[PDB]
Image: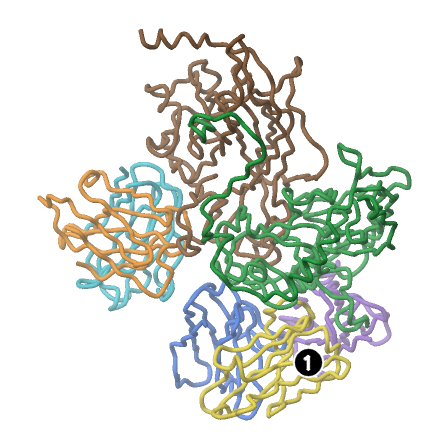
Chain colours: A brown, B green, C cyan, D blue, E purple, F orange, G yellow
Amino acid sequence: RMGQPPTPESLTEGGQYYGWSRGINLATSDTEDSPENNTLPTWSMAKLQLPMLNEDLTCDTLQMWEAVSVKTEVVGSGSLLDVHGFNKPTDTVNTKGISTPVEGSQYHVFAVGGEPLDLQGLVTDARTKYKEEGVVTIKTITKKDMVNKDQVLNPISKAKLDKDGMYPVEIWHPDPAKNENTRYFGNYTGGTTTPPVLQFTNTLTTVLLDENGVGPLCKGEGLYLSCVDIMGWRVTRNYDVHHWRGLPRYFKITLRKRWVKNPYPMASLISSLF
Amino acid sequence: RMGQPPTPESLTEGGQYYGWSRGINLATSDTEDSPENNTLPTWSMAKLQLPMLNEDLTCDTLQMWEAVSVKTEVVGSGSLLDVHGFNKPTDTVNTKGISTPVEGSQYHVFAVGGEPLDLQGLVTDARTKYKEEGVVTIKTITKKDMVNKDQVLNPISKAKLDKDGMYPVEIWHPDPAKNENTRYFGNYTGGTTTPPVLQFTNTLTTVLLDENGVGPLCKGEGLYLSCVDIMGWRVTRNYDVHHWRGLPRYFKITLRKRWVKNPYPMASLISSLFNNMLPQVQGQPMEGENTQVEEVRVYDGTEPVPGDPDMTRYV
Amino acid sequence: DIVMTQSPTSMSISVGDRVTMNCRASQNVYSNVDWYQQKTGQSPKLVIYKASNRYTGVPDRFTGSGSGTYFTLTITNIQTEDLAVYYCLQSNAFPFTF
Amino acid sequence: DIVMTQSPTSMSISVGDRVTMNCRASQNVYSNVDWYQQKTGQSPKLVIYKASNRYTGVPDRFTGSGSGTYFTLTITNIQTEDLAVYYCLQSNAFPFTF
Amino acid sequence: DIVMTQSPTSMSISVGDRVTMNCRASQNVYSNVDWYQQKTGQSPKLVIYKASNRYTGVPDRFTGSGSGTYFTLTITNIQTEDLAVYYCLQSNAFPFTF
Amino acid sequence: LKLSCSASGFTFSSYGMHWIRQVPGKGLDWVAYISSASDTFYADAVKERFTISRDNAKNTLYLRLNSLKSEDTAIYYCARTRYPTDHFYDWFPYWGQGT
Amino acid sequence: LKLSCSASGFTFSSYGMHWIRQVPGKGLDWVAYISSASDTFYADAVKERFTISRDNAKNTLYLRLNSLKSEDTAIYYCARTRYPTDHFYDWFPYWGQGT
């Protein structure tokens, strides 16, 4: 979910940028930045609601799910071998050759957890004016404006990943301090013509356990998957408009049932009454 | 098998692009895309038919092959050191220097399995008009057109790798959800002048076992090998036509014989008999989209009288 | 908002002569300036787009030049069909101003 | 299909004079426009290929110019061997049109 | 083998006048064409190498131009020391032909 | 109070459309703009009153007027940008007829 | 009903060949095209009737005509592209004689 929403299904509204961003329009001066929400790649999230399990309240304990391992894979690398089409050609002096493939800054993050990903706000210039609708920024959560400390690290610009497609990846990064029931992996590769690189495999798997051998216990009963897979840009022909590109990510989570200690004194419901 | 088929054997029809693509012709407008099947690199597949093995039907079990390991290697890397020839030179202002070697987007996939590779359809713009003959696209399998969901992931745009040279690699990618009796490895490297990189070795081998220690059991009796090895492009001189290049891949599969449990109750052949004499019924939809089966419940033992008889995930 | 000021408010000239009308913008517009011709009773026709090119069908007497803060439109030999009003438009930030 | 419209349907001129014939295309053809000369009774000879170059053997009086939607072919000093019909052809998408 | 055909077989002209001799090749020679001058009784002197440059010591009246299939050598104002035969040579594939 | 600008001959939803008004003696005056990915940009003196929109699959702009219309009256043209981009600045050469 | 265009002096199978017809008073009119990797592109008004082909090792085009030939009659030329590419747009300078 990077820019163009999936709702206008017809491939005539714009050529159906679903899977791509809508464009990019640089600032007109130092202070004038309005990034037009359908331009910003955002976080993808989903929550699989697992069933209820046993409870053993006669002596305090409880059963809950436990994400033991994960096989993930970005699907659709070979589709970037589409070198026909109306993109900027490789020989522009004659407008001939190859329609340049997807290149540029890449950003691959995924995260498997028992509770939504905790995010932290960082930005380039904090004078950027993001729209106040359809997107979640640092002003939406800290009701005041953005300050200079939001350019480096503000321990008050925190959030969760509850929504989907609303937290742009250029503002909200996975929180290192907070995430305890979440294993997140990521990597960024900047540049302007950096060739993409992907590897897919049926075999190798990630282990989500920690040094105590637990792994994300699914709180409530849900299991939260989050991801962002930005593969580069696409330079059109009339001007150098620079739509983003993103590929889907396949998750396969292996979970089991673990006996834990019930934290809350459920008798405290009388306190709720009180 | 990337573009030019191997049939016109004479090296005079075009200079014999066997091993290469035929060309590349960019779209003429936003909506006009006709990629000309001999331009699209496609999947290579082959099936080695192994013999029959023992059956022990007196007590249910069965013997079948089992791909234990594989040594693979792309043959012909050094051939890209052919730097004479009529390609775009390295110094175009004088048309002198070196005829630029093969560079560009590379795509190396191989797969060893007991059944054909399951593929999933993804594309760049779904307004591309692929020819409706000699190639298999998402329209050939889902008889309708291509929709926007085919640009990201449509769980209905699935296929197998039965044919060979007909499934272009820009549409059909190995399915992560489906492939269970198949081990596939791959890697893609984009760009426009990305230098190719290959390593070959007589020694190191891949292991095709899984976490239970089984490895692909050859169903039927065949063993299915699939591959695609795109090494880059080749820029000709008159215009910047951009033929692809692909190198063959050598497989060496080590298999053994494993005793398994015979899944099918071969007595069910009488059912086949009962399925042959009984008519072919139309009936009313009882399975699928408009199913007319309200509910199905299976009772097995004797549980005590429950309270609310349907209490599950609370949300 | 950017304000575009044109120096010749009204210039009287004959056929075969040269005219040059200039435009100054408050802030910097890099090369995004268009030159529109409007004859009385018609929709304004585009003449010189992006301050340096001639739209299709426009003769070779029209010339757009300049970049930054000072743009200019020049006609070497006037024609009878060149008797119209001429505006310059900045299309470099919103809102656009003529 | 792209439609090419030429402005001079028939131009009467003498030797030593200048002529300019223009062509407009419905959609955009970047630089793929050819200029063909046909004398009565001969196969059409190519004159100006790709809208900016002179084919071999064609004299220096012929000139092709333009790009996009408006192309033009110019002759500075006519010759007696320049008394033929002249077509412009877009070769930028299929089907080709003259 | 490539065959080079020159259009002026023999041209009579005076001093101070302009001459242009052209050459056509059967196949394509990109820019590898040399222009040789031979006065009777001397080894052929090089004049214009690679079809676009003047060899050292050659005056500024000589000019080589063209590329591909049609090459040309031009002299603006003839000199008395320019009364020699002139050949064009393709050096682009073997065997070389004059 | 609700304008309309029907267009034909191209793909309507791929281009950006401006509304420009001209008072017959005061010259031209820009009003509004809507791009292919519909996002409205208005002029400073008309921000809260006008609302420019487009309705794809019917090929019509809708400049819903002030709903007050106190001091705004002029010839209202529509203009289409030259290229089918998401670039906001595209030197619209295809003006309307006027209303 | 079945044309023929014999060619000599080059490698026939490496070039793209067009068929262009001219009605003596209506000017020139493009008909069809076949490229080195034989793939046929026809004109809009002649799509289903003509079939252009080439037969390598004999160096001949074959524009199998309408099989009806109701209202199509003109001088039919063949043309060869300039360079031996798989680029479809190559400004054919080598026209035939006519038929």
Three-letter code, disc 1: Arg
Name the residue located 60 percent from the left edge and 79 percent from the top edge.
G18
- The residue at the far right in this view is B202
Tell me: residue E51, above or below residue F81: below
- Going by the image, does D58 lie left or right of C27? right
* Quadrant in which residue C68 is drawn: top left
Residue visible at 58% across and 88% down in the picture: G65
Question: Circle 1 — which element?
Answer: strand
| Residue at 50% in and 10% down | A263
| Residue G27 sits above or below residue C22 on the image | below
Q: Nearer the viewer, residue A77 or A91?
A: A77
**Quadrant that contains the C terminus of chain E:** bottom right
Q: Chain of mark 1?
A: G
Decide which of B249, F70 is in the foreground and name it.
B249
Front residue of A137 and A160: A160
Q: Is residue B192 above or below residue D63?
A: above
Look at the image and tell me whether residue A124 can be seen.
no
Residue A212 in picture, x, y percent from top left: 66, 13
Residue B70 lies in quadrant: top right
Place residue A255 in its image quadrant. top right
- What x and y, as percent, mark residue B164? 73, 60
- In the rendered image, which residue does mark 1 sit on? G54
Residue E49's x, y, as percent? 75, 63
In this rendering, the count of numbered labels is: 1
Q: Residues within 10 Å of mark 1 (few under 14, many from 20)?
A: many
